[PDB]
Image (cartoon, rainbow over all chains, first blue to last red; front, side, top):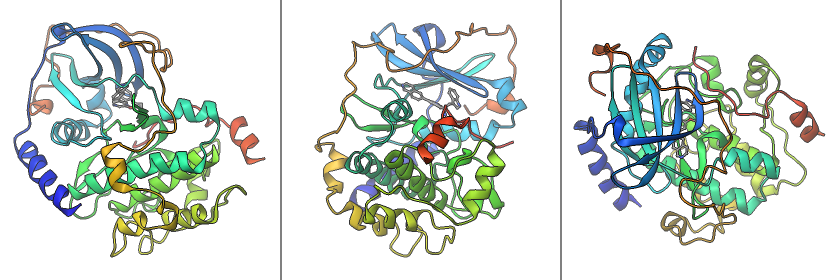
Length: 336
Length: 20
Ligand SMILES: N[C@H](COc1cncc(-c2ccc3cnccc3c2)c1)CC1C=Nc2ccccc21
C-alpha cells in the first residue's frame, strides 16, 4: 500500500502545483438534461460533439458563489479534482469558465445515486454495505494520504457505476490541509461532534461520516435524525447511539468506535490510523486488494438503457443557461 | 418503529449541505 500511495502522492503533487486550466469550451457540448441542482449551481448530462461522449457538466454561477462566500471552496474543488486520480472518485475531464459561470465536466455515471437505490430498497444487507463502505475506506486512505479532507460523505454524493462500484462526487468542501481547520461545513446528519461544537477539527470527521454512512446503509435510516437540524445536532453530541436488532455484533462494534465523540479513541484517528478499520472483525472477509482492482463481485448492477440514458436520475426543472455580455467576477476566479 | 418514524419525518429526501 505504502508503495502505491507514495507514487500517487508524486503525481497529485505535480498537478496540484501546476493545475490545468481552460481545457474546453461551452459550445463544444450539447446540453441534454439536468441531473441535479445545488445552492449555486446545477449538473447536466451533456454530449461532447467531437467524441460523441456523454459527461456530467457542473455549472456554477459565479455571482451566487460570491454571495454565498464559497469562492475559495470552489477554487479548492477544481484544483483538487484536476489533480487526484482514484477508481472510486469521479473524474474531472474538462474545466473552463465564461463571463457568467464556472464549469466542471465530469465523467457521467448512468447508474444513479446510492441515495435513490437505498431509499427505494430500504436498507442494504451487511455484505452489501460492507462492499461499498470498503470502497470509501480506501478512498479516504487515499485522500487523507494527500492531506485532503473530503467533508461531505453521504448517499446523495455516491453514484453506482456500470460495474456496481461506487464513484464519489461533490468536492465542494474538499480541502488540502495539514493541521486543524474550522470551516463549519457538511450535512446535518453526517456532522461530527467537533464540527457542531466549533472546536477545530481534522480528517477524523471523515471517519465519523463513514460511521454514519455504514449505519444508514445497514439500517435504512441515519443514527441521528429529527425534523430540524438543531435537534439532530443535539443527538450527535450526546454521545448516544441506538442500533437496530438485526445489526451483527461486529457491525455494532465497528460503529461504536467510528461514532466516537472522543476523537482520541475514534477509529481512523488513532496511532494505527486506517488499519484499525481495515483490520476490524467486520472486515475480515474483505479483500482490500481485490476491492481496489474491482475484481470483487458487485451485489447490485444498475443495468441501463443505453449511453446518455438518465432513467436512474430524477427530473429537475430545466433552467435556461445565459451568459452576460460582461465578465462578472474575474479577479475572484482568475486561477480557475 | 424507528423505520416508521424516519419515513414519516421531513428528512427522507435529498439533504442539503450547510455552512452559513
Ligand atoms: N450534493 C448534491 C450533489 O452534488 C454534486 C456536486 N458536484 C458534482 C456532482 C456530480 C458529479 C458527477 C456526476 C456524474 N454523473 C451524474 C451526476 C453527477 C453529479 C454532484 C447536490 C449539490 C450540491 N451542490 C451542487 C452543485 C451543482 C449540482 C448539484 C449540487
